[PDB]
Length: 137
Ligand SMILES: [Zn+2]
Ligand SMILES: [Zn+2]
Ligand SMILES: [Zn+2]
Ligand SMILES: [Zn+2]
Ligand SMILES: [Zn+2]
Ligand SMILES: [Zn+2]
Image 1 (cartoon, rainbow, N blue to C red):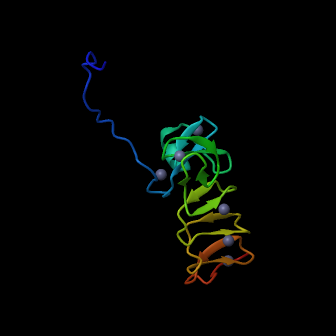
Image 2: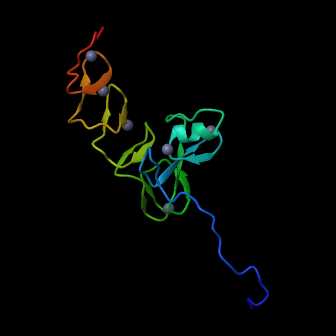
């Protein structure tokens, strides 16, 4: 029986629970460049000598169990919803904070459409106060 262990006690090994300041998600981007797990491309870039790109990543993990899977919205294993908003091309799964996948910009990013519109013949998305005030050539 357990009566010869002697190493009986507690561990104080602190670790990040879920999400990040950059993206509130229950997943980490698995970078195939080093098979490593980071919420953000810049949170990868800080630790690594090389860059993560949001088209190069293919897989993700679920921070709520650590199960490795392909880039999907839910952990089929423990039903972990990675975010409200999902998008495979941009490889972002996080909370919907009024964000929109613009067709001409070809991406989505945390951007309230009530404040942000696409300036036509410009390929950019600006604020309603800006009104598209550019040299749009
Ligand atoms: Zn981050
Ligand atoms: Zn890497
Ligand atoms: Zn899971
Ligand atoms: Zn997108
Ligand atoms: Zn746009
Ligand atoms: Zn413009």
